Amino acid sequence: SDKIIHLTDDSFDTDVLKADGAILVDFWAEWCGHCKMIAPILDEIADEYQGKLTVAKLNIDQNPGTAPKYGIRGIPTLLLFKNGEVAATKVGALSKGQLKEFLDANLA
């Protein structure tokens, strides 16, 4: 949880849209049960993908402003950004293996 950038509505443009390369963003809240499943999964991915992928987190309760701009209907939603632009999205939980697949499908 230390390698993950903690985003706010205020920082999101700088840490995501101004960000060079690839950023995995996780939209989550404290009441979301399956957000707790993928949190440790996201910690391990940040661990292993360190240097070719940044993992970042956004709490939608503390930061209500960003998720509507991407028409996010449910959490957890993962958005993979490349050079401030959406490369891919994933709505719902997944396993660690599945997330690696997801990333390979996009890391050309």
Image: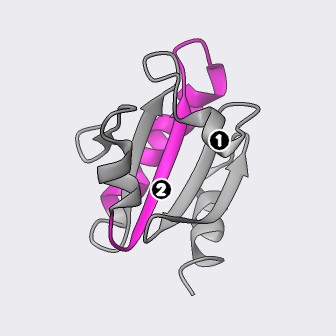
Amino acid type for the residue under numbered disc 1: Thr
- Please tell me which residue is depicted at 70% across the width and 37% down the height of the picture: 72
* Residue 43 visible in the shown view: no
Q: Looking at the image, is 97 positioned above or below residue 5?
A: below
Of labels 2 and 1, earlier in sequence is: 2
Which image quadrant: the C terminus? bottom right
Nearer to the camera, 21 or 30: 21
The secondary structure type at the circle numbered 1 is strand
**Quarter of the image where the N terminus is located:** top left
Q: Is residue 38 above or below residue 44?
A: above
Q: How many marks?
A: 2
Query: In the picture provided, is 66 more to the left or to the right than 77?
Result: left
The residue under the point 43% across, 71% down is 83
Q: Residues within 10 Å of mark 1 (few under 14, many from 20)?
A: some
Q: Pointer 1: what residue?
A: 77
* Residue range highlighted in magenta: 19-47
Residue sitting farthest toward the left: 2
Residue farthest to the bottom, as pictured: 108
On screen, residue 15 above or below 35: below
Q: Which amino acid does the dot numbered 2 rest on?
A: Leu
Residue 24 - label: 2
Q: Is residue 33 magenta?
A: yes
